Amino acid sequence: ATFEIVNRCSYTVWAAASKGDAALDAGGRQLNSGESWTINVEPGTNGGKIWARTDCYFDDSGSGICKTGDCGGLLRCKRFGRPPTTLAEFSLNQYGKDYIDISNIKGFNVPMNFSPTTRGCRGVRCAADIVGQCPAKLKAPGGGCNDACTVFQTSEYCCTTGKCGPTEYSRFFKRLCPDAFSYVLDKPTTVTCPGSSNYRVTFCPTA
């Protein structure tokens, strides 16, 4: 499928696309305010993720660091990024259809809109100012708003026993962004799209 990753934020971010054990397309790229990055994610891609990284510093070899969403210090990500990271999640060509969602399970760093550029389904969005409203204990010193699992490492927040319920912290993310997963067992906000649909991920959609 084809994804256009657009940065509408007034400042540069560093986009990243990965399925965990490898990079999607180039994997990562610098995106200045207003720039667009088109990529082709191989069909059949399961567990793909697209996100933004903030305050990055890379040398000529694509090696460095970012304050949010850093992926092993590489410009071109081969792995998922370090929280907090608003996540555009998706799986393509699964039993004839695709499904997408936005997740705050790994925290929030930048507002986002994840929508299809073809027909057959609607998009999802989480454009509230979660960083600005972030509770003191979840505020990431490097910028962003950490999820409770990242901050406290408990079975409840991380839902490690496969059994957990909503929490005061997950409720913060759910209240500001109803259409995004607030915790692991959150009521699905997944959207089912026709197989092989195309999409556009927009950072700071309401800017």
Image (cartoon, rainbow, N blue to C red):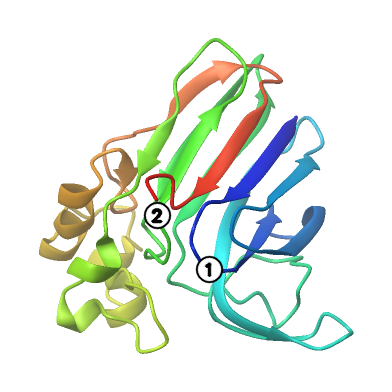
Amino acid, disc 2: Pro
Q: Earlier in the sequence, mark 1 or mark 2?
A: 1
On the image, numbered disc 2 is attached to which residue? 111
Mark 2, residues whose alpha carbon is within 10 Å: few (<14), some, or many (≥20)?
Answer: many
Q: Secondary structure at mark 2?
A: loop
The residue drawn where x is 52% and y is 52% is: 8
Number of residue marks: 2
Q: Nearer the viewer, residue 116 or 203?
A: 203
**Front position in the image: 40 or 10:** 10
Q: Where is mark 1, residue-wise?
A: 11
Please tell me whether mark 1 sits on a helix, a strand or a loop.
loop
**Coordinates of residue 96 in the picture (x, y in percent):** 66, 14
Taking the image as shown, residue 92 lies to the left or right of residue 140, namely right
- The correct choice, above or below, for 101 with respect to 144 in the image is above
User: Which amino acid type is shown beneath numbered disc 1?
Assistant: Tyr
* Corner quadrant of residue 108: bottom left
Residue 43 at x, y percent in the picture: 79, 30
Q: Is 80 situated left or right of 87 in this image?
A: right
